[PDB]
Image (cartoon, rainbow over the protein chains, first blue to last red):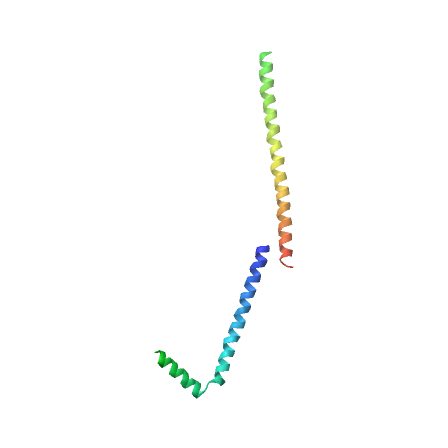
Length: 52
Length: 52
């Protein structure tokens, strides 16, 4: 029974960190959506070509 | 009287034997009693420690 309790704790921690990860990356996308910028964007292009 | 001793001895051994054979049956049953008691008190415990 104690093993089962500990297993439920692990399971719930994991299924929680999943929710936060989902919302986290969706929010980071919504952040890029309005920090995107022709100058910074062209800088991305420059860096990727320079690394190419 | 030789065979008085012989016969009474044989049947007296058999009675000791049967008395053992029935001393065993009570033993098997008592095991079942106490072991099912332990099973009950195990399930009834688990199913509320876990609910807690």
